[PDB]
Structures are given as C-alpha cells and as structure tokens.
C-alpha cells in the first residue's frame, strides 16, 4: 500500500431542524467552503439529514407520535434528489465526503452513513447495529452484513457512530479488517471524550471526533409546557478534535458551542511505529479465544430474480 | 413517494347467472352509476362475470359435469368483447376498476382479477393460489410470479379473495411490498368479517370488504330435487363496508340482502401513525426466520422465439 | 373460438407402385368419390406419393441402391406439376385435404404431410421428426420449427404419423397447441390400434386411423429370390376406423384387406366433457417438471438478402 | 448390469373397510401364501391400508366429512405397529414387497407406496404427483424428490399409480433412469387395459398390472339412502394381468370378481431385442425438444441445525 | 397420537405490585382452588409474577430509571425459592400449569414463560421474540431456539404472548409443529378479540386466553403527579374466554372487572372436522413460497466445557 | 511410492541488505546459475528477503523501533512482484525452489517459508512455530494447522529452521508424516552443526543445511557507537553442508569466509537400510506414551461466507 500524506477536516454545525431542502443546501455550502481550503476528506455529525430526534427524550411514549409523522415525510431514500445534490457537491471539489442521514426503504426507517468518492459515485453505506436508550422508540434494527472498510487513494477508510464504541466486539471486528483513518459521529448529549480517545489507542488510527450543537429553532417547537423547556436546558455541549494514534490531540478544539471547522496534517506512514507495541488481531492474541463473524445479506424476504410483467396498451385492445 | 386523498366505492350486486352477454352490460351500468357520484376507484365481488359456481356444493362429482358446458362456453379470454367493452367504460369515466372473472387459456380454466387504469389500458392480473375446497373440481392451480402490486396516482394498490386471508405466507409476501390500499372479495357463503378485520390490523391498509347476494335466477335452475333445493336455502348472506388501519368501520354498512353501493373518503397520509407500533416485514422481525419468494415464470411448456409461417397463395400456384 | 359439427372421411387405398403420374390421377378420382358424399375433410394413408419403400428392409443395404435410383426420379417438389392437380381438386370440391408425400429439397430427400384449404391454397407442411429402422437410410432428418397446428373453420387441425405416437415429448408438444381433431397415418406393417387409441385418451381428440394395403405389382417389382418372395408374405395387413375422445370407435371398421372409405359425424362441441377429468397442459400438472420447446428454423446454411443477377443480351454486344 | 431370471406375483383382494388393525393382519396371510409358492416379488392394489375412499364419489362435499373423521384415525402414521407387522413378513420369507397406503404427516394425509427388501428395511418411498377427480379434496401433493427408481437383485424397480400413466412427462421422467420391471396399480373403476399396454410398449418393460375389488360390506357403510345405493354398484372391476414388453399377456387372466393371484416367469434379458427398435431418451431423441427436471427437496418449512432440549429436576431441591 | 378429554381453566387476577413474595403466595392459593374444582390445565396472565411495568409509558425515559431499580431486585433467577414454591403446588394436585415472569439471567433481564409437569419437573422455557413500543426499554430479545412445542397427555401444548399474534411468521412457525391446545396471555391494555379469534381459525386449535386487571394500589406508586394520576385512568381492560376451532366461545366470558375463573370441557378429536377444509403447512401450500427456520442456539458468548477449581485449605498452608 | 535419484544444491549467500528489489533480482540470478549445472532442488538460507534483523541483538528495545519502520515497508506482501519474479525463475528452469522471507498479512509480520513447484505454482507455505530470544520483539507465533510435507516427483519433502530443532515434539510431529529429504536453514550466529546432525540420525533423512554470511553493508548501518561497532564483530561465522542417514557428510564444505554453492548425488532408495534399526513413529515405541496433534485452522477472527457489495456509478445516479 502507498502510505499517503494529506490534510482532513471535521465540521461542527446544526441543520435547519426537520426541514430537508434547507438542510441539504446548507450541507452543499459547507462542502464548497470546507474544500476551498484544500482538505481531501470532510466529515459531518450524527443524523445531519434532517436532524437527531430530541423529542423521544423529553416526552412519554405517546408524545412521539405527534412528531414521528413530521419526521417520516422528510426522511431520505436512495433514488432521491438529496443524493443527487450531494453527488454534484463532491464531483465539483474532488474530496471524499462522509455524511449521516435517516433513510427509508420498505415501510421501516433506519439510521445510516454514506460515503461519496471524488468521481461522484456512492461507494457503499453502513447501518447502526442496535439503538441506544431513547431512539429504540423510532429507528429500526441493524445488520452484520454491511459493516465495510474501503480501500482508497487515502488509505483504508471506515467509520462508526454514537455508543457503538461502548461494545468490544465491534472494535475487534473493525480492527480485523485493517482500518487506518477513522470517523466517529456523536449527537452531542453523550459524554463523547473518553470512549473516542480510547478507540485510537486500542486500534492505532487517527480519529476525527465530530459532534453537533443546539439552537432555538428546535427547542421552541420540541416542547409544549414549562417543565419540558427548562428540562431541555439541562443538556450539554460537545467538542470536535483530531486525535493521533498516541491518544493526544493534533488539532486545536472548536470553541464554545459555535459553528466552525477544524483541520490538521494526516501523515499515515507514522502508524507503523505504534503497531510495534500491540496488534490485537495479530501477534498480541491467544489460541483459546476467537470470534465468529458472518458477512451475508439476510433480509426477511429474499427475492429470486424478480422480473417485470406484461401491459396491454389501449391501442392494441 | 406521495400521499393522496380521494373517495372510493365498493358494490354489493348479483350477475345475470351464467349468461355473460347480459352480465357485462349490467357491469357497465354499475360503473357509469358508481363514477357519477365522483368516486376514484370501484371494486366488484368474487367471480362476478359468469357468476360463482354454487352447483359444486349441492351435488356429487358427477352432477357438475352437466352444468360445466354452460360455464366453459361463457368464460372470458384475453382479448374479447368483454375486455374492450369494460375498457370503454373505464376510459369514459377516468376511475380505477377491479373486476373478477373466470379466464380460459389453453384448454384449461382459471380464476383471475383484472385491473384497468384511467387511460383504458390493462395494468396486469392476479390468479388465485390454491382453489379452496369445492372449487378444486372446476378451476386450475395458481402461479407464484403473478402476485403484483401497482404503483399508481392513488398510492400502492393490490388485492386477494376467499381463503387467501387464512394463510400467513401470502399475507407476509404481499406485505413484503409496500401496499397501502387493498381490495378483498368474497362469495356470500364464507365467514369473512374476522379475517378481513385481522388483515387490516396486521398489514396497515384500508380494506374494501366486497361480496355478492343470491337470486331466484340461481335457485330455479341450479337444483332439481326437493332436498337439493331445501339444502341450498340454508346458506347465509354476506356484508360490504370499508375499514381503517385501526380495525374499525369508516363507511356505513350496506343492508344484509339488497343491491347497492357504499363509499367513504380515504386519506392514505394517515397510515404512518399506525405504522409506528409494528412493521412485520421491517423492524419487528427477528434474524431466526426468513422467506424464499421465487418470481420466475414457469409455465409447463415455454416457447422460445415465436415465429410465423409462409403460404403459397392460389394465385401464385 | 367456435364449435362446429361436420362429416369427415378416412381412406384405405394403394398407389400404382413407384409411378407418380398414374398415382396423382388415382387420388383425383378417389377424392371426387369421397367428396361426392358431402364429407368436409378427407385424409390419405402414409407415403402415398409415390409409395412406401418396402425394398429398404427385405434386402441387405447394397440391394437398396438400385431401387433408390428409381424412387429419386419420382419424388415431388414444392412447385411441381403434382401439386397443381391436387390444388385444383380441392378448389373444385371445397373440402380440407390432407396428403402424404416424399419431397426433394437441395438434392436431399424427406417425408412430409401437406395440407390444402377450400380456397385451393397450401396451408403448411410437417416433416417426420425421426426415421424408424426401415427408413433411416432412405430419408433425411426432421426439424423442430415445422410442427404446426392450424386454426380453421372446422376447429384446430393437426397430425403426427407412424412411430411418432410412441414418443411422449411430441404428445406434449402437440397438446400444448390446443389441437381438437388429429389425423394419424400408418404404412400398414407396424402394430397401430393400441398406440392410436391411447393417443385419443391422452389429448382428448377425435382421431382417424388411416393405412395402406399390399398389392400384386409391388411384390412382382420388389422380390427377386424365392426366400425374399415367401418372406414378404410374413407381414400383417392394416385397417382403418375413427375414434371418439372416450377411446371407443364411432365409425364402422373397413374390411381388413379391400380398398374402401369410412366416414362419420363429428360434433367437436362434445370435447368439453372429457377436459373435466384430465388436461396435461393445464390444471393436471406439477411445477417440478417443464419442457424447452425451441421454435426457430436453422437450415444448415442460411441465405441473407437473396438477390438476382444481370446479363449482357446479345443485341447489346 | 444383471439379468436375473425369476418369478413374480400380482395380488387382488379387498381389505375389510376402514379398519387398519384388521387389514394389516390380512396382508400377512396373503404374503406368506404367495411366498410359499416360490415368487421373489409381490405387489398390492390401491390404498390397501386402510382402504380406498369410495364415499368421495357419492353425496355432497359435507356428507363426506363424517367419514373423513373415521379415515383420519386409521392412517398409517409411519413409523408404527403397522410398519413393523409388514417388515417382519419380508424378512421371514426373503421376498421384495410393494404395498400402498395413506401416509400421515403432521396435520395432513398423503397417498404413498412403501418398498421393502429381504433384509426387512425400507428401500424407499413414492407419492402422487397430483390427485384424481373426486379425492382432490381429500389428499395432499408430492414433489420431484419423491420419485425414485431403485436397483437391486431383481434388476431395476419402480412404479406409478392411477392416472399417472396418462401424463406424458411422467413416462419421460421414469424412462430417463433405465427402467426394467414396473409395478402399476388401479382402484378397478378406471380403464386399466389401454392405459397399461401403451406404457409397456413405450418403456419396453414387464408391467405388473394390479387391481382392487369392492366387497359387499362396503354397501352397508358408504351409502345411507336408497338412490345412493342404486347409483353405486354400477362400475367396472379391472383385470390384474401380467404384460410382456411386446404388449401381449404373459400369464393367465384372473377371474373377473374373486380373491386371487397370478404369477409367471420373468426373463429380463428379453428386453434388449426390443430396445433395438426405439428408445425415447436414447437414440430416438432430437435437439429441438428437452425437459427440465428439478428434484430439490422442497418441504414448506425446512429445519436446519436441529437441536435438542432438556428438563430441569430435583437435583438442587 | 391419542386425542384425550379434560377440563381446562383460565384465570383473571392481579398481582401485589412489585413485591415478589406476596405475589408468589397468592399463586399457590389460586392454583389449589382452581385444581380443587377438577381442572387439569391452568393458565396465568401477562408478566404475572413480579407484575407488568405500567410505569414504562406514563413517564419520560428518566422517570422510569427510578422504578427499574425496584423491578431488578424482584425478578426470578433460575432456580429460586419462587420456583420451589410453584413446583410443589403442581406435584400436590397433578395439574399442568403455565406462568409468566421476568427471568433474571446474568446481568440481563428477559420476559419468559415456565411450564410444569405433574411430577413437579420443569418442561421448558419460552422467551419473548421482540418487545412492543411501551417496553423496548426494559427487557432483552429472545432467539429461535427458545420456542418449543411439546407432546404430553393433554395433547400437544405450546404458547405465545402479547403482540406476537400480530406477525405472520410466528403463526407459521407454531403451526408447523402440529398444534392442538394453545394458550395466550395479554396485559389487558391492547384490544385482543380480533387477534385471538383469527388465530383460532388460522391454526384450528382450542385457544385459551387470559388477562390481568389494574388494582387501585398501583395508582399510589405509578403516578407521582396529578396529570399522570388522571391520564392513567383512561386505559382499556381485558377479557378471559375459551374459543373453539371456528371462533365460537365455549365458556361464558368472565363477567366482571374482578378476580375469577372460566371453565370448559375440551375434546380434542373435534378438531379433525375442521382440518378437512384447510391446512396452511400441509395440502394448502404452494411450491413458489417457503420458509427458512434456524434452531441453532445462539448465546452471545458460547463458552465451552468449564472445569472445577482446587483451593488450598488453611490446614495445608 | 517411487524412490527417485537426483542432484540437489545448497546455497551460501548474503542479500543486498534491506533493499527488497535488489534482493529478489540477486536471488533470480543465483537460481539461473545454480540450475545451469543440472541440480533439481535449490534451497536458500534464512530470511533472504529482505534480510535478518541483527539490530534486535545490538541495542535496547527503544533503539529497535527506529529500524522497524524501514523493515516493515520492505516486507513481502503476497501476491506481489517478489512472488511473480521467483515464480518466473522456477518456470524457466523446472527445478523445485525453496525460499524464506518476512511475509506480512493483516497488521503483523511473520517469518515464513515458501515452496515453488516446476509448473511455477506455490504448493504450500509454513510459518515459524516460535520466536527466538531477541527475535520475539519482531514476529508473531505460527500455528499447528500449517505444518505440511509434500508428496513430489522427488519423494516426500518438508522443512524447519533455527531453534525448531531444539524441541522434540516438532521432531516427532514432522517424522509422523514420513519426510524423506529435508532442508534446515539457519541465520548464521547460533551453534548449529551438532544440533543439525542429530536430526539426520533421529529421522533418517538426507539433510541440507544452509547459512548466511555477514557483510560491510550491515556493519556500517546497524550501529554507530564504538561500544556497538566492535561488539558486533564477536559473532561466529556459519557453515553449509549436506548429510546422509549415516550422520556423516557427503558434500564438500563451502569455505567458511565466503559465498558459494554445494552439490551431491541423492539416492532416496538408500534410506530403507538405516530405517531397519530405529524409527520412533513406527514399531520402536510403546502404548504408555502418546501425542495429541490438533491441526484445525483457527485464526483470531474467522470470516464465514463473504462476498462483495453494491456500488452506484455516477452516470446511473
């Protein structure tokens, strides 16, 4: 492999809440402004299209139905306009774009992460394994089949999200495929400091820690009563940083709950020095511990060579 | 996709028994009536064109062979006068139509239902799976590739009949699609409110429960002995009404033994609220059970590369 | 489709052995005799123009060569004078006609069945699919693209011949076309009652057993040594009669050696009774078994865009 | 290959109606007497355990239910006492045995054949490819994985039931496996002669044609009113004869309405003299016609990685 | 098979809320009184032993964390005093009993059923497949190994609970194992008349259905504020009935919002009258659709054989 | 087996230090000289691609990390140009060739040995079971699943290296597979002659032993302080020889200071004489001692069936 040298970037921003066309044009403007500095890769926070669902934490399980209706009409799907508008924005700038969204296929709704290559093509996508405490009331289940890492011009890319960092099985599964540069997206409320820093030491990779901020445009409609509004203000902000495989930050930190961007040099040839001490999927292991990994698509229904039907035109009849 | 709002009609009616040439004219009169009131979709009961074969229940296996002539000589085929005459009736009024019939192809006889679109073209057809209990003497076996749902101006459409609601396999196979509005048809004898109501709860859809009524045109011709006549009067009559995805009527109920139509406005946007609780082909599944759904058309004999033939005309000879 | 009623005739006769110009006029006298009684269809026995090659299996393979030389100068061709004298005989009586020929094409030789319409034009032809042990060194091979069934004023016509009735794949192919009336011609020696009677049950048609008689001139031609002559007398003689779809005769039986004609009423509306019990191409089938029926013509060499040529007339030069 | 020269026997008898425990014992005195005369192979008629359902052909689709209730408790339920009572009678005599019966799986009935050899174990099993005319409402359906041809000390072995001799593709499927000695069995109402002799000629094999009789003790059970009794008892009985590959009987005829047995010498080397003329799957083939044969076992629900359970008990207590 | 007769009992009750010892003591009293009346099978309502978590959906997701701390200390581990107290109450009366509870398992918590034999031994567990919208915060998810059906002197026994009746794949998985007598438990908030009556028809079984009632003491614990204390009055309440294999109720319904029991005589050979019409996994199947069922146990960590340990005693040190 | 006779060659050489392309082209030239004399097998010393890591012995473990970064970028990936050049060199000469190198799969390095057969293909691979005193800093352990011997045109072949001769369990395991001709590579420093010779007496195989030599290329970069510079010259020189089953040499010596090549006749038929006295895997043992040899392939993570993933091209999007 090449061991390339380049500079990457991580964006701290908020979407226009539950309003998809305003969100996708703001996303397009952020790519066109981030790539102007010559950064080769750009990353975004959790659930950025159309927005992370705070209403599940504030109300009892009947309250969500009043807003789930308004979310479900604004979700992404694969043959849509939102995908084409992001593909134009990558093609115009020649940068790897990594972006998060709610997606609909069949009747259910899922949380996903999408990767666009500099030729404008969609490389592949990742699904969250299992939902955290509140969001089980909204999003569907994951799968073990679609958990990729991609060989690229900029080394082996991959990514995870939220509390996926809390379970060791997915750390080993990802590390077994030789990931080298890694993106981690957080919503903002969870304590994102330590579990992010630890993943760098455990697997020797540069971590682009990425997290969102609150705005009045959500909280002035997320809540219907005084108890719910002041209770919302008990939540907290989150940082964004680039960490080295040693566990210290390379970048500055984006300050004080305000929209912005952070970037640094990535010199991936340096990763070799820290694989001298540990390699969990290699020499630093044991003969009495193993793992069973399955990579097969098992949807509920598996079509077998579906074909189109015959139509009798009104002229024939 | 898109979520329209419109009003739809279902009819309780009886055909001119075994006499196709009068029966198709009564069908055109019911379309030109039901569309007068502004309904966008219309649906008919089971086996409506020649009529359902009650003679299979009243006598032993030798008795039906006498009546089978009158049936076989009055079944429709594609194309015919029946198809072009119903296509005129849909083209004049700009409404979707679902109509059920006995269709003849090869030497065999089958049961189907046909879908006509507002441009007058025939969208496709569906053929019954397994042929119940008495019908096994009269009608041929189904096929698995002919199980469509249609994407339309009025959402996603499809339908089923008789005991097809008693088998979980076809219910799950249909809900593997994304069906939203549904037509179910019954002959008068089977007990039908429970299975149609359960289907609406399990696969969140508006169901147009539709069924037929008996007449002296049957009674004075279909039987000969006193005990055949006495036995035939023991059968009960049916119902017609339309249900929400909550399992409750939105229409009124048509009276229990009279010809007439029922209608209501339907607002397919509302399905999302009940999609919140369960989704059997989505997030409510478990990765220990799956399904195989083969869609390859396999007729008994498959022609390859159909070709015509030449003749030596008597002027050339 | 439509279900006519009509009178049909089958002929027991012999040609003037290996002479074509006598045998075509014998057929004209015999068809004007058959059609004088008002029969609407007439069918002749196997290889009637100019005769069946009994010499092919009385002697060893070298004995055949000297007789083959005299057969080859007496075969028919598509534009031959032998066709005009039959086409006029059909035109002058307005009946369907079925006749058997040996055809010469491209210097090779084949066995064929050949059909004429009441307007005098040639409807189409059929070629023997495979030769039996007497035939394999006289006549050429079949083709799959030459297996027609004709829609007509008198219902769906077709007809195999000879040993073809022992091969189930041809029964299925012919039944897939939905035939209704089926000619079946035999030379005379092969045992022919039981296979033609099974065919009537298997595809539910009327069938016309048609076969030839031995004569004095053909044995004086073909024998030479005494142990050829008294060996030829080993062969059994044939018979002709017509069967219903139930498997009993409807006609009388023609006496078992003399020249003659049999005829009966045919009432094709009656076929529907027996399609109730069984239909191999319809309901009486299994999804675990199929058949590939290629139907394109593949001559050994294929001309593309056939065109003529120019000549420099002597006046020009 | 082997050409074993032996003796085989056809049995006609009636089982006492709808009583498994009596019919099982009655089969033992027949097998022991037939084997005491030196026959190596023995065959039995239709559904001999417990009995063929004549009540399907008389009265309404409701009138049969009160009898179906009694049939269900008398099905064979493999493995059972009814299997081991037959298996020992093979082991004690060293004869091959074919017998046919109602097999029960889960909730459902199938009609099947069971094959046993001199070591007393099952060679294999067979099931119908479709029902007939009346019993189509009683029995279920087989699959292509349950149509074997065996090979053993008496040559190759197989068999078919009822109208399976009248479907062209089943003749073709069996002939692909190099058939030699064939069992065929009939309920006595249908016409066995024509259906069987053609199969002998089309396969070039000895056919062990076998048939049932109906005893006076049926009349007092199956018909409850005078006209039903006077519509019954107006049927054929069939012939239980043995046919050689030429289509001529090789044994005496059994008297038309009694218990009895027929047997003859079988000399398998004789078939070679006839396979010289024609072979439907060998040298008599053509490139334009084929057949797709699929025999993947297809249960509706298939278990994989079957596991066993345990009961907890008083160890702790 | 055997087809027995017995008396079955269905109980309507309420547990002492979140207090296991008080709830265990009530169950021994109720089993002895039900068994004293001659019933041989006794069912129980949903989550009965510690009580169902109503607090899970009156409050937002940080209100419930206060009460989870009480439920965790009141769950049943296997084995326990709670099991010992039930097991002897079965042995003292020789009644089969079914009961439902939160099974504590390692650090995790699952909803489950237990079945006891008349000898007091444990027949087997069952685990909830997927949690419904109110309860996805509390319990973990089961797997396809822990879904048994088992054979016993009452006939075949099995069970399902809550929303599991609303998805088609579980209906087919249970029906594939030849079902006969079925039990259903409901929490009493969900409308269950339709889902239970359709299941009775769709598998043809006696279905025995049960539910719990609220008790006024719950409203002193579950709701700590006025609007919650009023809102929690607006819920539905549940039924208790025994339904025959066609949807008619056999017993009276339990007549009041009180503790009580329903009784009926059950006679399993009645089911055969209805298995005649349809059998979803038997003869009513089709080839085009199937189902894959996997029964391999799948614990997250599959620890193999484990050994004991040796400790050095104080005397030897 | 066949007991062949042939010439074998043993090579003493040093690589161009740490330059992989210079080492593989030097190796490619050295085969083309060694094969020019007609020897059929050629074997190289330990770690010839790219070189043995002497720096691990000269300094403390934080000095090693400075050089590890350059060794890692020059390790042999498979497949690569380093494999294609050696495969060409075997294909051009039709001699078996045996070579050893630092392979790199996943994140770790391993020392390995590779065998190329005369058709140019790899017949197999071996990994060093256990690392040596300083060498434990650099490479991972092997596995029991990779310990081949090959059946060949030149008898049964295998191989071992370095301290693997000191442990008797690997002597016994290698002897259990009936090896006949053996290669034993060494780095150069370890005391080798007596430990190598004992393998010949214990296993009765022809043994080829081969060692590397020191150069100025390493001396002027492995160290820089005088304290290291003159310490490194302490290490002993190596030897290259070949031995028979007698424990006594058949080759000449290669001079101890220089590169060179050694030859002899090998006559495998001569092994069965010495195998008269002792062989520990055969008759010369007793049942009171045994060995357990498990050879399952157990990597740390085991991929199951895995394929590719779907990609959407920029024109389609």
Image (spheres, coloured by chain):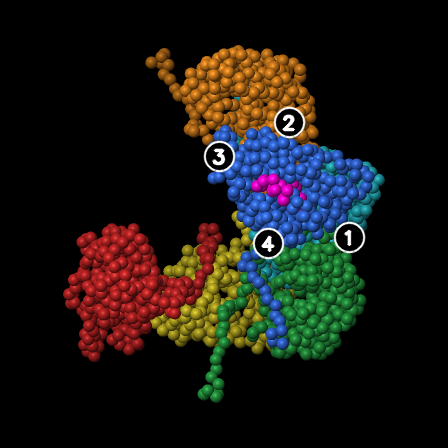
Chain colours: A yellow, B cyan, C orange, D blue, E green, F red
Q: Could you say where residue E17 lies in the image, as x and y percent from the top left?
A: 69, 76
* Tags 2 and 3 both on a single chain: no
Residue C183 falls in which quadrant of the image? Answer: top right
Q: Could you say where residue F147 lies in the image, as x and y percent from the top left?
A: 35, 62
**Which of the two labelled residues, at mark 4 and mark 3, occupies the earlier sequence position?**
3
Front-most of residues E36 and E200: E36
Numbered tag placed on residue D301 in the rendering: 4
Query: Which residue in the protein does label 1 denote?
Result: B253
* Tags 4 and 3 both on a single chain: yes
Q: Chain of mark 4?
A: D
Q: Chain of mark 2?
A: C
Q: Residue at x 44, y 19 (%)?
A: C64
Front-most of residues C312 and F103: F103
Q: Residue at x 68, y 24 (%)?
A: C250
Find the distance from the CA under tag 2 to the CA under tag 3.
Answer: 31 Å
Q: Could you say where residue B71 lies in the image, as x and y percent from the top left?
A: 72, 36
* Tags 4 and 1 both on a single chain: no
Find the distance from the CA under tag 4 to the CA under tag 1.
Answer: 40 Å
Numbered tag placed on residue C206 in the rendering: 2
Query: Which residue in the protein does label 3 denote?
Result: D282
Q: Secondary structure at mark 1?
A: loop
For disc 2, the neighbor class at 10 Å (few under 14, some 14 to 19, many from 20) is: many
Q: Does the stretch in magenta take in D35?
A: yes
Residues at marks 2 and 3 touching, judged by CB atoms closer than 8 Å = no
Residues at marks 4 and 2 touching, judged by CB atoms closer than 8 Å = no
Q: Is C198 drawn above or below residue E233 in the view shown?
A: above
Residues at marks 1 and 2 touching, judged by CB atoms closer than 8 Å = no
Q: Which residues are magenta?
A: D31-50
Q: Quick check: A104 left or right of E219?
A: left
């Amino acid at each position: 492999s090449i061991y390339p040298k380049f500079r990457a970037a991580a964006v701290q921003a908020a979407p226009i809440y539950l309003n998809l066309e305003a969100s996708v044009e703001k996303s397009c403007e952020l790519i066109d402004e981030a790539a102007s500095n010559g950064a080769k890769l750009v990353a975004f926070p959790e659930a950025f299209l159309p927005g992370y669902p705070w209403f599940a934490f504030i109300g009892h399980p009947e309250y969500t139905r009043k807003f789930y209706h308004e979310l479900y009409k604004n979700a992404v799907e694969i043959p849509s306009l939102a995908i084409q508008k992001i593909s134009e924005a990558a093609k115009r700038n020649e940068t790897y774009v990594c972006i998060s969204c709610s997606e609909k296929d069949g009747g259910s709704l899922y949380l996903a992460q999408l990767w666009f290559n500099p030729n404008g093509d969609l490389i592949g996508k990742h699904r969250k394994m299992r939902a955290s405490v509140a969001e089980r009331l909204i999003w569907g289940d994951g799968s073990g089949s679609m958990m990729p890492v991609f060989q690229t011009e900029i080394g082996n890319l991959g990514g995870l999200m939220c509390w996926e960092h809390q379970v060791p099985l997915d750390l080993m599964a990802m590390n077994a495929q030789n990931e080298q540069v890694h993106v981690a997206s957080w919503p903002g409320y969870f304590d994102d400091e330590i579990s992010s820093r630890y993943y760098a030491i455990a697997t020797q990779t540069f971590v682009l820690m990425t997290s969102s901020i609150y705005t009045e445009e959500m909280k002035e409609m997320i809540c219907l009563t005084q108890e719910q509004r002041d209770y919302f203000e008990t939540f907290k902000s989150g940082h964004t940083c680039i960490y080295g495989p040693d566990g210290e930050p390379i970048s500055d930190m984006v300050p004080a709950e305000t929209e912005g961007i952070a970037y640094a040099e990535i010199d991936v040839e340096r990763v070799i020095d820290y694989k001298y001490y540990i390699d969990p999927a290699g020499h630093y292991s044991n003969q009495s511990l193993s793992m069973n990994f399955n990579q097969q698509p098992t949807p509920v229904v598996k079509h077998l060579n579906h074909q189109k039907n015959e139509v009798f035109t009104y002229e024939d009849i």
